[PDB]
Image 1 (cartoon, rainbow, N blue to C red):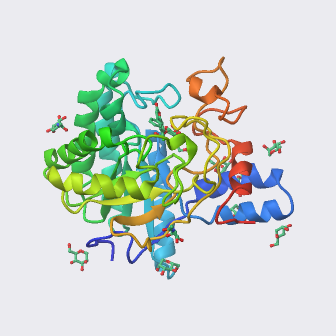
Image 2 (image 1 turned 45 degrees about the vertical axis):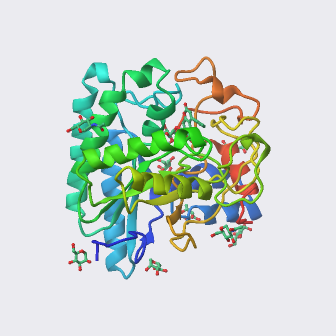
Length: 363
Ligand SMILES: O=c1cc(-c2ccccc2)c2cc(Cl)c(O[C@@H]3O[C@H](CO)[C@@H](O[C@@H]4O[C@H](CO)[C@@H](O)[C@H](O)[C@H]4O)[C@H](O)[C@H]3O)cc2o1
Ligand SMILES: *[C@@H]1O[C@H](CO)[C@@H](O)[C@H](O)[C@H]1NC(C)=O
Ligand SMILES: *[C@@H]1O[C@H](CO)[C@@H](O)[C@H](O)[C@H]1NC(C)=O
Ligand SMILES: *[C@H]1O[C@H](CO)[C@@H](O)[C@H](O)[C@@H]1O
Ligand SMILES: *[C@H]1O[C@H](CO)[C@@H](O)[C@H](O)[C@@H]1O
Ligand SMILES: *[C@H]1O[C@H](CO)[C@@H](O)[C@H](O)[C@@H]1O
Ligand SMILES: *[C@H]1O[C@H](CO)[C@@H](O)[C@H](O)[C@@H]1O
Ligand SMILES: *[C@H]1O[C@H](CO)[C@@H](O)[C@H](O)[C@@H]1O
Ligand SMILES: *[C@H]1O[C@H](CO)[C@@H](O)[C@H](O)[C@@H]1O
Ligand SMILES: *[C@H]1O[C@H](CO)[C@@H](O)[C@H](O)[C@@H]1O
């Protein structure tokens, strides 16, 4: 059954899409031989989230759900995993991941049409349980990054757009997780309560949507889930892993009106601990990382619904070419792997790095 109560990951199996599988098989494997080539083929089996970073990706969302329907009637029981990520004036704190819609060019109205498009696909496939991460970095940027003019002038649009996303996708087969940054971002004691207030306000302002399950953490980041020793670059923060973050912000969400909020955590680039990060704020194509804890609903945690792979390992975080569009200085740093292609595009060297440093190992 597509509908659910409680943990939406219980009773289903996350779907490994053909989009990532095509990338690995056609862009990575032809370049690899021997033990590496076989290890790479195994990675394409690991379920990860499909990103709807453009409106042109929604037909591919439908294609993926078409594959799930076929698989479910052949005997299986699979669930869809997608990311809603096409906000007007997207990626307001950086320059690497600016999107197609801008507030000045009717972006809010274009975002609502984008949401309407997704809703129709979700109604078309109401027989399939659909798991969604809502707008990465957006709300986390509104907490700490209002000093950036792009974020400040995007606050009203973000909040109206997110509200439209959580109410229009509030369907019986949907489970939503608002992006909530990570331990190195909002995990700091000073950021915890202001972050909790904002998430709870989004929840309350949308009339407590029953499909809105909770928060997603560490999306496209590198933090360890439950590492016992604090890495050098976490110096000053008692919240140095993802487990500590969710158990801190959790009761704070309840304080501000959001009871029964649960968490998912990205671990697809968290295998090697500590990372090659020279500063904790460095996010672009970070060196010294590997594939981490495999997706599983058996977490052994009171608040974690599932380990997930949101960011598909191999897809770039941003270009290191200073003569290219959308260039961010974060991608030219010593701990950023070079040379790096455009954000979202395939980064061959980075995939090889992730596979070699994988823990659990594929080799
Ligand atoms: O300006 C920032 C700052 C931070 C940050 C703040 C505080 C502490 C540490 C870091 C950022 C952190 C993170 Cl995790 C950021 O995520 C990057 O941005 C996007 C997702 O929001 C990712 O790019 C997208 O990847 C998708 C999947 O491959 C593609 O579909 C999409 O085309 C592409 O835009 C990127 O990989 C993350 O690294 C951004 C921060 O920005
Ligand atoms: C509350 O909802 C309205 C839409 O009804 C939206 O425009 C506004 O941004 C929301 N406020 C907050 C604080 O999220
Ligand atoms: C961390 O979590 C993983 C996966 O749930 C588990 O194998 C390991 O025992 C945990 N370690 C600690 C120290 O809690
Ligand atoms: C999905 O949810 C509905 C209730 O909304 C049930 O009727 C069904 O059995 C399943 O649990
Ligand atoms: C999802 O599908 C997998 C493979 O069929 C199962 O192992 C799991 O129990 C769930 O039904
Ligand atoms: C399968 O999909 C990937 C990602 O779009 C492509 O890179 C590949 O060429 C094939 O079409
Ligand atoms: C791409 O195709 C190859 C061979 O068919 C697989 O090994 C891989 O898992 C991916 O699906
Ligand atoms: C990668 O893309 C090629 C087509 O360019 C396919 O032949 C292959 O199966 C994989 O999807
Ligand atoms: C795979 O990687 C090799 C280098 O290792 C390239 O030459 C090839 O074009 C493909 O990207
Ligand atoms: C990994 O193993 C496969 C066999 O499944 C080989 O075909 C490949 O060459 C690599 O050694």
